[PDB]
Length: 558
View 1 (spheres, rainbow, N blue to C red):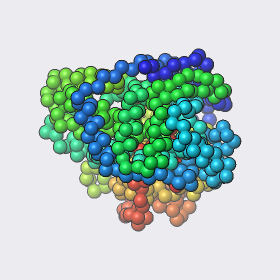
View 2 (cartoon, rainbow, N blue to C red):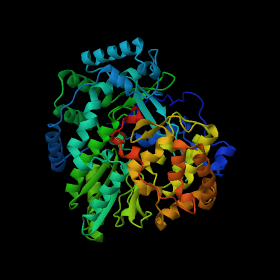
View 3 (cartoon, rainbow, N blue to C red):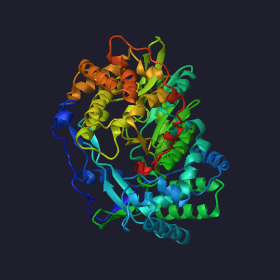
């Protein structure tokens, strides 16, 4: 069947869409080449619609069958419950798309009687009607990048009333099921440092390691109606209340497996027969379907002793090299099997024999030294897109701050420590808003953090070593240097000059601001302080930050 059919109505915007980074002194200080920065808009939505629209043919085999059977047997051990309406309401992001039935996220969150009664109505209708397709909206995402222009991604999502109902039915399953069926392979359980440890231990376990990442072309489009019904059968293998069973079946048949799409002006735009990117189960579902297909393909291809890390559509596999030519052959074989299972490639996979060169979720492992001279490994990535988004968000504030998420995930990197932290601590000081909670996205969910708690957050996630790394790798330094030159950013030496002042300003503000100055900016001074463990970091519970997200990142914790 076709992933999509289109009536010919356009994908339309809601309000104005800015395409270009404005020329402003506050963003110019970070990077000067503003003409290189763009935002995707609905103007390119038809280009993306072309790419995501195609016929799927899937042919399954004995290798897929055995993996699936193992998975359902593992799902047998999970038991789950429904959420109360109040619990699902608390999971709703404060800036989530409003409902067409007269209320928005603020009303959901405050438990307004209108919103609550509406959501009870939606729930009752899912219990009663297990077949009528549910309406969705299709929109073009506005995301910022640097010219290397890519067309906008498309997001398809149901009404806010429906989205709360999905959480009520599937949030508890989502907390339990992935780990129970995939164990260590489920990648969203790991904090950055735990991801690093996983990969280092997997790579180290092989006599002659080989790794590869597999890039599925438009993974959501390749998910078939059968794949989605199979996901359902996995959720039903759990021990669930009958009411949950019914609603899961209804959401599957009415929403997950496909349905009509409307544009922002209320015109019928098309019909979907593939994964919706803005449904609660998008991340759990993609992770499960990827895992199953991937593990079956390893077995088809003769990959020897695979260790997989699956995060939604992103897959990495580390295994025993069988020789240069035979690895090449085996990856071609793995590709043919994936292609049979309806997960055809974008970039072809290639065997990699150096761990630093393996990319999982746009990230890689790198090494440096801490202040005691010990080798420490950390997660890093190419800093282009983070610095470009940081520049855009400096001038156009977003309800969700990508730069904060980058600080937290990538704190031990040179580019976070020297560029992002310096730039944003200066801004916070100028605004006098150091002590104000901000929202950010981590692993498909939205969280709230106070910048003044960053040192304990970082120590907890990355250790005290994160404040003292030095002697970074030439791969890493080359990449940071190349980004600064591409974007026209100041050189690292200039960021050090700036940071010395930010550090002083922080120390003079006292209290928690001074801990931020002393720990976050120890790298900036000649006579380094001896940093000791922060008592608060030892008491922090941050596990909750690393879960499967929701589709469109439409879930909010705390």
